[PDB]
Amino acid sequence: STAIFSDRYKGQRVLGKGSFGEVILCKDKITGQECAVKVISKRQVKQKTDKESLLREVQLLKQLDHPNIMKLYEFFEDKGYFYLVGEVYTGGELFDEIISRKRFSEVDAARIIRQVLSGITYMHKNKIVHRDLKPENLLLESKSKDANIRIIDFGLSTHFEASKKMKDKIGTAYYIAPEVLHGTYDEKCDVWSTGVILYILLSGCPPFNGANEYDILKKVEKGKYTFELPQWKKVSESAKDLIRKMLTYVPSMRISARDALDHEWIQTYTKDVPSLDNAILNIRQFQGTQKLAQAALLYMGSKLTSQDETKELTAIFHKMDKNGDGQLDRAELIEGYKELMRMKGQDASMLDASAVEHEVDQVLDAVDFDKNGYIEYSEFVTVAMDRKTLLSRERLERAFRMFDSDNSGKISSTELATIFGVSDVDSETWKSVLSEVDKNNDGEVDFDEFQQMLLKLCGN
Ligand SMILES: CCOc1ccc2cc(-c3nn(C[C@H](C(C)C)N(C)C)c4ncnc(N)c34)ccc2c1
Image 1 (cartoon, rainbow, N blue to C red):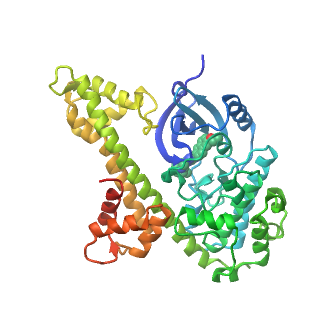
Image 2: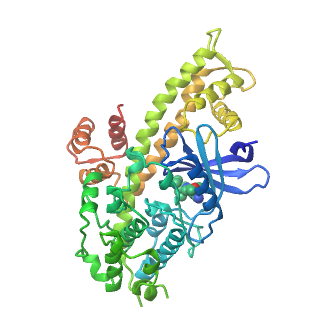
Image 3: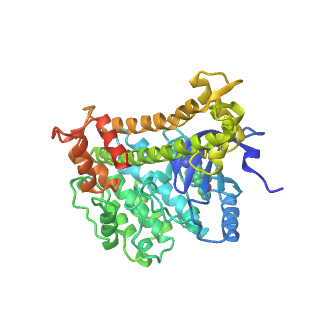
């Protein structure tokens, strides 16, 4: 009688890893409506509150409505997962659209920040705090150029513990309010994060920066920042005054979301403004660096998952092969692949039996052999996993290219230091690894070299 997610929805495709879980594009089996489902693994994420409190929050968020906040439609739960079913948005992340623009002025910044403050104000009225507000939580509603910003992930932080794994942690330290670090926080922390994002939109650099996560956290905690850089000369006084008010240390003296909406800067500039060319270049650099460290971490992770899943799948099938001749049929292959999912959460794309039948067919319709006869599972295993190895190898490659804006084919030692600082790989550890692959003292690596470093940084 309790509703089953897969009874209602089929998976179309994965949309990536978000905070607390993967997101999958799904479709209602009856009505045909498309949805973006965030699937949270119960094993991998400790809850902060009881079930009663989670349920009550979900019920509230189902009834909330605001143009700058993601719409939530449905909530499911079974033995291992939460399924959070929201509206699909196709505009991508705000910053990925900002990097691909000729001009960007304070008028562009003010319109974006007004949308963010508007969504935030509304949620604070409803006593919902974000805590983790950052640029990848700002999606554009569509590919249209006038598109509304939809803030994602309101509600989650209250109920779920943040990951301390670096794959999940990257990019977060720049944005977290000081009082979150120390444990006594309330809705003002969201003004702080919004202040950091605005600082970044108008200069291209984080106001609190450092060589690794803990050095960023130290800057945040002392709370000092300056507008002394060159690009701050191209910016109105009123913009810096707002930022000062939003990055006020003691939360009770910090400006509220609502009072920020009535600020001179927002009033004036969301109604003869020079472009901010110097900020577009730095944000393009900043985004590129952030995106490649993520891809570096996700690539290392999927290689670790592959090692785990390759050995496990082989063992499962050996048990199944009773006669010991290596011959299993598609139905057994499906049963073996299902069992791998029975004890693993990395394929949130494999939501049910029919997602797995199709995925076996795809592997099978590559290995060439017939799916109505018996099969050599050894072969099947070696192709199934690579459809994540090659798949992930290609996603790293693209971010390497994206990062290499001069198409030089290479990343300097200085740039590696920056990528590995953001990735929290120890300086001595990656230099050590660099030495084992770059024996010419070029002080630069090409893609395959950079890839070899990462395999050596995840025990290969
Ligand atoms: C209470 C929070 O419940 C939800 C439900 C669905 C969610 C869906 C997304 C989401 N994530 N993504 C993919 C994004 C990015 C590619 C835009 N990242 C996380 C891989 C989306 N793309 C389009 N529309 C969406 N709604 C999303 C993010 C947070 C969500 C939170």
